[PDB]
Amino acid sequence: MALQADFDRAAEDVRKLKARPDDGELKELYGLYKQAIVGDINIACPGMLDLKGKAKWEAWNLKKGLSTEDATSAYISKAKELIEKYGI
Amino acid sequence: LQADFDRAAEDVRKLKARPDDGELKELYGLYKQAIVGDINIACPGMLDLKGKAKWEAWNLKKGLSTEDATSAYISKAKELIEKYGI
Amino acid sequence: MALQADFDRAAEDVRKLKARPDDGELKELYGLYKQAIVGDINIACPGMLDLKGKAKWEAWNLKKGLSTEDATSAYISKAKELIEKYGI
Amino acid sequence: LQADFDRAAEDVRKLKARPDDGELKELYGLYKQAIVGDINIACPGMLDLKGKAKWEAWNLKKGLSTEDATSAYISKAKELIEKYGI
């Protein structure tokens, strides 16, 4: 019950911050809060476990708006970088 | 450029070691953007950045007991209070 | 080019409807419009191909808010229905 | 109720034929709601009903040529105009 009280106080006190925590800090705070109060997520969110598909979308979405030419140019530079690093 | 792209795309198959995950992501993203262009549909949720972030954040803590998660929240909250002030 | 013109006219004329088409009609209209102008969807949207996971979420989400008792009661009636239909 | 649920859940494993998809969905949804309760997280996108509907609608037409999709759009549009009026 000591922990419960300290949790209740921490949760309200973090509302008083004089500056906004960065994204990763807000994620850690949120994750812990839910896990503490709710426990494990209780359903497999479709796709969320599709790590390959998510990675491809994220990777490709990052390049949204790059023209054909600029994406082609960049691919070559990246490929050359990996070839230099690892060898062929 | 086209010829250099075709050669680079084939040559990268010859690598003597597997690039790390971030390296493969950058290569894949550029390859698709080059050959295909913009993704042509809004993938449901994928643009739901708030919802995605919450799921990732919370999924990372899968398996922590109530007590450990409670204890850790308090430490994190106190950590943020020390860092930013109240 | 005859088809293109008829498409352009149909697409603008459907805006003039005196009543809103039902959901399935709007879906068919939208699907055809995109397929005509854009072609195939060009990325696998994570999860969207996870048909098992999507079906479970949809099935369970439909029951959101049912109390334990009412969901338990209903499960039994449903199970009894399937047992009567198919046999055991 | 609990006992009747436990018996029903086991007995439905004994079915002599596989229920259709909608039947399995209803059974599954009720089972989870009974044992687990409400889904405890908003699954990204799943609540994006507009985006989901668009993807489903468009995915259904995967593989139609430009011409066939164009021709069919016109027929559908004319169909809706005849039905609802303009």
Image (spheres, coloured by chain):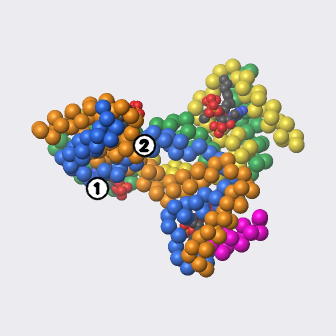
Chain colours: A orange, B blue, C yellow, D green
How many numbered marks are there? Answer: 2
Residue at 35% from the left image edge and 50% from the top image edge:
B59
Local crowd size for mark 1, using a 10 Å CA cut-off: few (<14), some (14–19), many (≥20): few
Tell me the magenta residue range: B1-12
- What secondary structure is the magenta-colored segment mainly? helix
Q: Is residue A38 left or right of residue B18?
A: left
Q: Is residue C52 left or right of residue B37?
A: left
Q: Which residue is mark 1?
A: D14
Q: Position of residue D61 (x, y in %)?
A: 65, 47
- Reply above or below: C29 against B63: above
Secondary structure of the residue carrying numbered label 2: helix
Q: Residue D35: within the magenta?
A: no
Q: CA distance from mark 2 to mark 1?
A: 51 Å
Q: Is residue B68 left or right of residue B3?
A: left
Q: C88 or A17, which lies in front?
A: A17
Q: C38 or A29, which lies in front?
A: A29
Residue at 59% from the left image edge and 40% from the top image edge:
D54
